[PDB]
Image 1 (cartoon, helix red, strand yellow):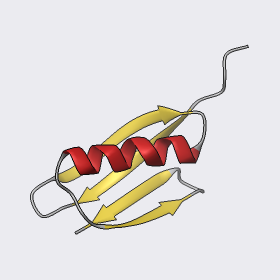
Image 2: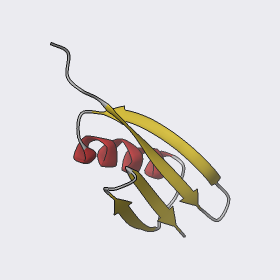
Image 3: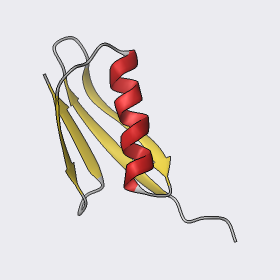
Image 4: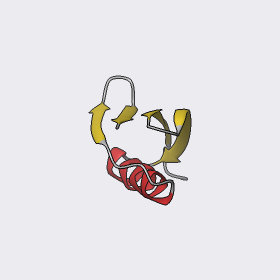
Length: 61
């Protein structure tokens, strides 16, 4: 079987970068690493939440 994958969302409230993006992953930790890399690649340094009910991460500066 292929692994079950989930779509995770990132809500970004940055100083210059704003909006939403998505990633697909087998688990939340994998998604978190992809989103933290995305934020670092775009110069975002903020604080984070994760809601397991909605599969949504949020970062604010």
